[PDB]
Image (cartoon, rainbow, N blue to C red):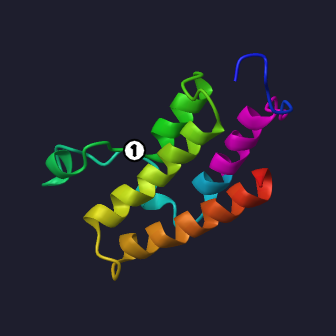
Amino acid sequence: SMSVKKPKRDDSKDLALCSMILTEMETHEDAWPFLLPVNLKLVPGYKKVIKKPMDFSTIREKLSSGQYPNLETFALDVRLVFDNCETFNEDDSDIGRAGHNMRKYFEKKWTDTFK
């Protein structure tokens, strides 16, 4: 509350560390469905169904331009990429499996870097 604060967690490396995680996600072999925005002209149904499209390149641009206020808003966008994927793709598809794999990969890096 006012003049009553928990001890100050050092957040000075968060930007660099989120960048490294995102590099690792970018370079994973199963990243290909997620590297670029889904082409809304060429994928029927996507525009209407997926209310907030997100992809790695859009996260990278947001990161690099100070559009994440903190590490939680960065995690929310990464998770959005996978939630979108699950919304549109059957589990039993290459893209559906890619999404599950990437989410797992991300959540472990997240816990190990920050928890």
Residue at the top extreme, as displayed: 3
Residue at 52% over, 29% down = 62
Q: Is residue 6 above or below residue 35?
A: above
**Between 37 and 80, the one nearer to me in the picture:** 80
Q: Is residue 45 left or right of residue 113?
A: left
> Which quadrant is the N terminus positioned in?
top right
Q: Is residue 14 above or below residue 108?
A: above
Residue at 63% over, 62% down = 107
Q: Is residue 9 above or below residue 24?
A: above
Residue at 31% over, 42% down = 52
Q: Secondary structure at mark 1?
A: loop
> Where, by quadrant of the figure, is residue 97 drawn?
bottom left
Residue 61 on the magenta segment: no
Spot occupied by residue 51 in the image (x, y as percentages of width and height): 25, 44
Spot occupied by residue 35 in the image (x, y as percentages of width and height): 47, 50
Q: Is residue 43 left or right of residue 61?
A: left
Q: Is residue 42 left or right of residue 1?
A: left
Residue at 39% over, 58% down = 83
Q: Is residue 99 above or below residue 24?
A: below
The residue stretch that appears in magenta: 9-23
Residue denoted by label 1: 54
